[PDB]
Length: 221
Length: 221
Ligand SMILES: Nc1ncnc2c1ncn2[C@@H]1O[C@H](COP(=O)(O)O)[C@@H](OP(=O)(O)O)[C@H]1O
Ligand SMILES: Nc1ncnc2c1ncn2[C@@H]1O[C@H](COP(=O)(O)O)[C@@H](OP(=O)(O)O)[C@H]1O
Ligand SMILES: [Mg+2]
Ligand SMILES: [Mg+2]
Ligand SMILES: [Mg+2]
Ligand SMILES: [Mg+2]
Image (tube, rainbow over all chains, first blue to last red):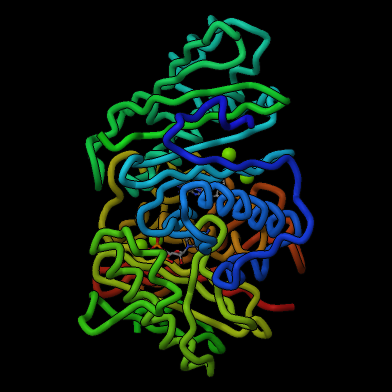
């Protein structure tokens, strides 16, 4: 699994690389995609099939996963998690809220960013630091995935906007040259609605099978 | 009502000015606010009481209003609408999809914008044009409201991001000095999922009772 390369043992994950046949929303989810085009319906249903497989590994039965503030997923009591879908990937990660405070994941095609996007998503200091990272890796795309995972882990604990310029992400590469760690240093007020302040979020990144994947798992102390 | 000052006929509106006692979510809505702090629970529940009053006026029984892509409200079959909540205001507008293509509304306290917001939401040309507008009005705040109503009317028809810089808003002021019209000229690809391109959205604005309110109601062709 691509997500096993960026996750700890305390969470369950499930992923697919396509839209498997015969998948349906649960009845409670139907209104969220009643008006959605085929591509949106597919990713929504497929990623929630993945979520319910991962929930099953936690000993949680099939439940609907609705959407709340700014699109955040709505987990059953005692569960936290994150969802992501891009071209060739749907993935879900869940953990017990007794062991895990927040999860944020992202997956993107491992390709150069469209012209203009890098400058829009970076601090000057990030552009400099990227230029000195090693490997034939699309560091622009990897940075984008890390910013996205950071927002997904941050938002359920704060319900505040985190802009691209509001986190400074630094990367470390493990011996493989294709995976490692990142740290997101939060540059804005770090007060959380629950648990300790979010001054910094540590995560993992991996580039494998034409995808960049990032995950942050914030643990309950 | 404050919303009646910015609306045509064939839409229903409802509003209140606080969070009254004696309100509950519908049971299908409970998951959306199950982890929410009181201020968020209260605004969510009150604005949906408003939405159900406006639906009742239109002839639609009380239904849950869930959230979909990027937080967009999920309306019942044959209905479009918009919701807003700020300090001292909750309001809802709904129409039949047979009369109305889309609806966007916004309400803000009529106060100067907080630091840095005006520059984040404007083109250079807009900052120039706003300096030219007449009256002791917070034109920075009214522009923010018109950009918010624009995005809410646009998003359901496109499912594409509209940045604050992707819409050029121009205002008219009526002889009252506290109401008028605006036009939002769209600067990105205007193609809709159905019907004619969204090249420009026309709306109304009003300042009354310490609030700025904006509404766009788009015609069903
Ligand atoms: N504000 C937010 N906080 C955390 N997760 C969010 C979020 N808004 C959206 N998400 C999650 O991000 C998912 C999409 O991830 P990505 O954009 O990387 O493919 C959404 O999938 P769904 O819309 O299917 O629920 C949703 O579950
Ligand atoms: N992408 C989107 N498109 C249209 N309406 C949206 C939207 N995201 C959020 N909204 C609506 O805007 C409301 C909030 O408006 P405002 O920010 O002006 O107070 C939300 O209220 P709820 O979160 O209570 O559903 C939701 O109904
Ligand atoms: Mg996706
Ligand atoms: Mg993503
Ligand atoms: Mg609000
Ligand atoms: Mg608003």
